[PDB]
Length: 86
Image 1 (cartoon, rainbow, N blue to C red):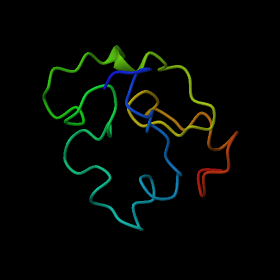
Image 2: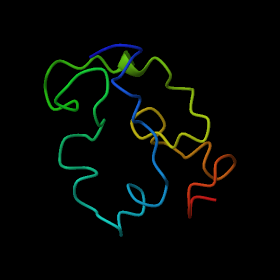
Image 3: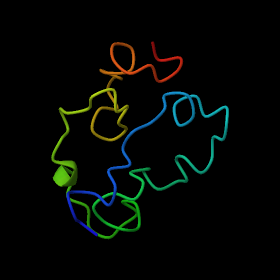
Image 4: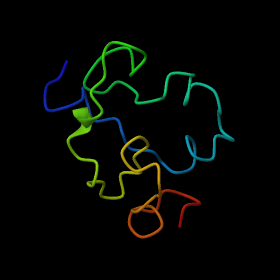
């Protein structure tokens, strides 16, 4: 764990599943503030998060983040074609 930053940097949504949630709407948010398998296991449940564990809040690249840029897509509507976020 905590290799580069998270385990595999799974902070990238298709903009058509975790955002649309019509395809699932349950395991995505799974009642744990989301965060997926990032720098620590538990998925931000309560191991002792630090918020800056991403070290790339202002960095995306058509990544479609969730905790670092929940304010806006800032990459889907003007970068990678996620789905309906264009």
